[PDB]
Amino acid sequence: QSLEESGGRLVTPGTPLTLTCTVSGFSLNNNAMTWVRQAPGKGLEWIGLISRSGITHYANWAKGRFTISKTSTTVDLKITTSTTEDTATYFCARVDYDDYRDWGSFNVWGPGTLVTVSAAVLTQTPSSVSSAVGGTVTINCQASQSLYNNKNLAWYQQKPGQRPKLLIYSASTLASGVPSRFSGSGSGTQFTLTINGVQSDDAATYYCQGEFSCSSADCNAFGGGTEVVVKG
Amino acid sequence: FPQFSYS
Ligand SMILES: [Cl-]
């Protein structure tokens, strides 16, 4: 039910580095884990994941320069060689599937560990929007290719300096403890997140995330995110 | 299926 991550690491260019993600309250025997990074000021980007049996999958950009390994309680991310482009916060997350169905989403998140070194796309629009309290906010996510199961598009909320939080999965399913003022729709390659009656606490960045077919694309990708401001 | 468990 909770993930723990190693401390922040200030490293030289060219030096190998291992990030740890410790798991409380479940076994990795029955759960897949994924890594996601976020450079400062920028958006979420998928790195890769490890299946229950231990099969690894990477984004194309990452293949070879990152290795994911695990034991039953801990998953790692080895960065082979560290460049300035590896300056980011690295989050781990539980991958939401089991033996019957695959929700596509990531539903438990670690707090992230900052590293300062010193095809399938989601187009997300708009890049930013300002709303009056009580107003309506629509965010669009547009795939370049149909998603796994046709509908494994999830939305996450991320307030500044906090980890991402899952809101919607399978396009239209509201996550645990999420206010009903959020709702999501779409199918194929067009999905929208709507906020009906926006509140001051809804000020965040919202990312869409799509699961694709691993054997024709990156298994996951995120949109570039939407900054939502709330005028009050 | 799960597509993750196959290479
Ligand atoms: Cl190390």
Image (spheres, rainbow, N blue to C red):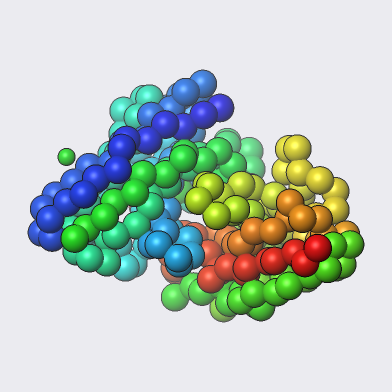
Residue lying farthest front? Answer: A232
The quadrant of the image that shows the N terminus of chain A is top right
Q: Is residue A82 above or below residue A192?
A: above
Query: Can residue A46 be seen here?
Result: yes
Q: Is residue A2 left or right of residue A201?
A: left
Residue A81: which quarter of the image?
bottom left
Q: Is residue A118 above or below residue A102?
A: below
Residue at x 38%, y 29% (from the top left corner)? A22
The percent position of residue A66, horizontal first and vertical second, equals 25, 54
Query: Can residue A146 be seen here?
Result: no
The percent position of residue A161, horizontal first and vertical second, equals 50, 51
Q: Is residue A148 left or right of residue A181?
A: left
Residue at x 48%, y 61% (from the top left corner)? A44
In which quadrant of this rendering is ligand 1 seen?
A: top left
The percent position of residue A97, horizontal first and vertical second, equals 57, 41
Residue at x 49%, y 73% (from the top left corner)? A120
Residue at x 40%, y 62% (from the top left corner)? A40
The percent position of residue A231, horizontal first and vertical second, equals 77, 67
Q: Is residue A69 left or right of residue A121?
A: left
The total of numbered circles placed on residues is 0
The quadrant of the image that shows the C terminus of chain A is bottom right
Q: Is residue A53 left or right of residue A159?
A: left
The one nearer the camera, A55 or A128, is: A128
Residue lying farthest top? Answer: A25
